[PDB]
Amino acid sequence: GGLEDYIDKAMDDVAPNLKALVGAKLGARLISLAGGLKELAMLPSSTIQVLGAHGVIYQYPAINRSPWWQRGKIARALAGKLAIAARVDYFSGEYIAEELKKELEARIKEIKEKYPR
């Protein structure tokens, strides 16, 4: 039983939607940065977008593998999904996660870019 295994398991109990969305380590980092599941669940999302600091969600693959200029938009979309994720985890306890689907889909929208003028 390593540190990481503990947290992976804990996220299974505390916040499985988050965990599904961004993974247990990023999920757990955001909860800590928030101060807890509840506090995370109360945050606007613009606030979520900056929790790490670009806050830690920029480390998100789709953002990082992406042009500056597409990133802030991808951040916003992610933070939103995160805000919903934490809310369902706190208040409802249900399992949505395939708003990854909603989410992918937006990313693909946003990929309407070449470098702004």
Image: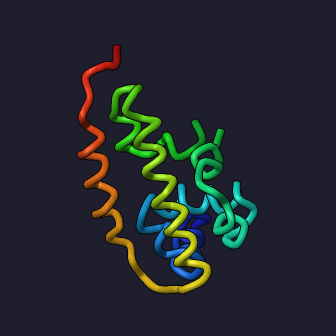
**How far from the left and from the top, in percent, is residue 12?**
51, 78
Considering the image in quadrants, where does the C terminus appear?
A: top left
Residue in front for this viewpoint, 13 or 113: 113
- Give the quadrant of residue 98: bottom left
**Count of number-bearing discs:** 0
Residue 90 at x, y = what percent?
61, 79
| Residue positioned 38% across, 72% down in the render | 97
Q: Residue furthest top?
A: 117
Displayed quadrant of residue 104: bottom left
What residue is at 66 percent from the left and 64 percent from the top?
A: 40
Residue at 53%, 55% in the rendered image? 26
On-image quarter of the N terminus: bottom right
- Give me the residue at 67% from left, 60% from top: 43
| Rendered location of residue 20, percent (x, y) | 42, 68
Q: Is residue 32 left or right of residue 48?
A: right
103 displayed left or right of 75? left
- Residue 61, image x, y percentages: 38, 44
